[PDB]
Amino acid sequence: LAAALAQAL
Image (cartoon, rainbow, N blue to C red; front, side, top):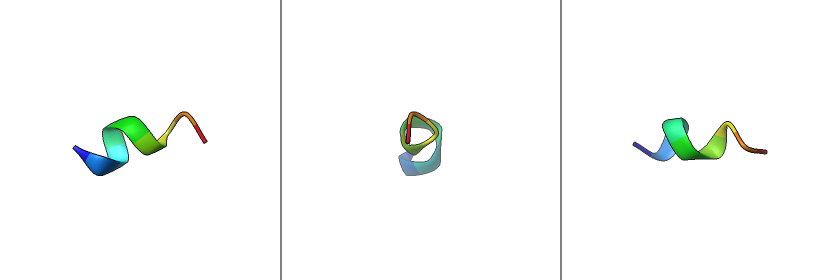
């Protein structure tokens, strides 16, 4: 999940 969101950065 972290990665899935972190892609924004």
